[PDB]
Amino acid sequence: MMQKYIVYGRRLPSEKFPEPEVFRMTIYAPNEIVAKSRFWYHLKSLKKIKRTHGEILDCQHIEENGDFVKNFGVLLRYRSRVGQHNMYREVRETTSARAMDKVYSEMAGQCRARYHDIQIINVKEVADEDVRREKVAMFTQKGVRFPHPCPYVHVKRAARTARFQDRAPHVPQ
RNA sequence: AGUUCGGCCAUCCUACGGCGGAAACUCCUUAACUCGUUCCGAAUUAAGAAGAGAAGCGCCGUCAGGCCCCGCCAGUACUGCGAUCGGAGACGUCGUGGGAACACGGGGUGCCGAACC
Ligand SMILES: [K+]
């Protein structure tokens, strides 16, 4: 559901400063209306330009090619009930937006932090040798094999319409 | 440049060093008359022209105190509207608007209007 957007903005031009500077950002958001709001949240803190005093020049939407599985490293900050913290996370996904979906669900589940509690500092691709987290690194290898981690899930699902049967089914492994 | 009468009432004030005076303003000289000092010609009232740039006044100066403008401080402190956001609470968070002060660093240091020499 996440999407990559590039936003340009600038302070409204005046007599003291004709041709103000242009600032660009990369944003991940579910749509164009949330993305432009998040651009004004940062430009107000980092550059002290409220939304009343500036204008947005573009909301570029960028669609990425998948088809191969890469590593990503996300540097972010979030807020808990006792303060603010920094954190680095690693994930394997096919596009950057999909890697941000995975991050937001792990923050929501293990830290209970929602979307507006989180500021993304950095998102970059990480080559296989340079990985630093054990979970990701296991799969950055040649020849990884494991048996199915939950084959019971197949059997139960079929038993939701086939409510009564004549023998208890097996779980092939 | 100067004197009398004013407007706005320190970018004009206060302190200490300087520099100036043809004219002008001042300081200054006098106790007959006028009038005056809880005592005193100090002040003030009258009458004058020997002397002055020592003061006041105008100008210049000072890592000067004050005062005045700008930037920073800072989209920080605080706050209007909305929330079946978090927390035992005290309190905090997010969305959408408004937005300081102290401190700090650089600059500056009266102008306008009538009449006369
Ligand atoms: K003098």
Image (spheres, coloured by chain):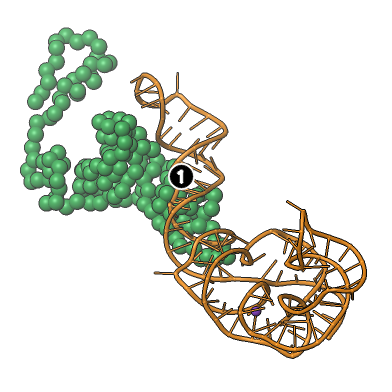
Chain colours: A green, B orange
User: What's the residue type where badge 1 is placed?
Assistant: Ser
Horizontal side of B10 relative to B94 (left or right) equals right
Horizontal side of B93 relative to A70 (left or right) equals right
Tally the marks: 1
Q: Residues within 10 Å of mark 1 (few under 14, many from 20)?
A: few
Q: Nearer the viewer, residue A55 or B109?
A: B109
Which chain letter matches label 1?
Answer: A
Answer yes or no: disc 1 within 8 Å of ligand 1: no
Residue A87: quarter of image: top left
Q: Nearer the viewer, residue A127 or B70?
A: B70
Horizontal side of B50 relative to A116 (left or right) equals right
Q: In x, y percent, where is residue B100?
A: 52, 48
Q: Nearer the viewer, residue B99 or B55?
A: B55
* Res. A53 in view: yes
Rendered position, A71 above or below B81: below
The residue at 19%/51% (across/down) is A126
Q: In x, y percent, where is residue A50?
A: 50, 49
The residue at 29%/50% (across/down) is A122
The residue at 8%/40% (across/down) is A144
* Res. A94 in view: no
Q: In x, y percent, where is residue B62?
A: 47, 73
Ligand 1: which quarter? Answer: bottom right
Horizontal side of A79 relative to A50 (left or right) equals left
Q: In x, y percent, where is residue A90?
A: 21, 43
Quadrant of the snapshot with the N terminus of chain A: top left
Rendered position, B43 above or below A111: below
Q: Which residue is mark 1?
A: A37
Quadrant of the snapshot with the C terminus of chain A: top left
Label 1: element kind: helix
